[PDB]
Length: 99
Image (tube, rainbow, N blue to C red; front, side, top):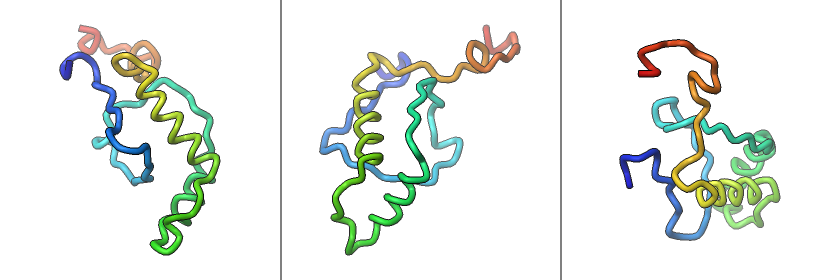
């Protein structure tokens, strides 16, 4: 179950969120799915809320929507959604990679 595709993690607790500055190597895959969510507003909401005194503000609709979208996406794919394939979506031509 762990060596076939990427086991889509389903959080065992409540579906919270963080916004982290990730490196390319810490990110497993670039999924093909396109969720046209507004990053600017999500940043202008997360960074605002992460004041310890204002950590308990009511969630913003864009942030809640993104969190819900990610959680269902984890639920919505049996073994992991396709990544933006180097060959079949990014149009590359290395033969060794096909092998």
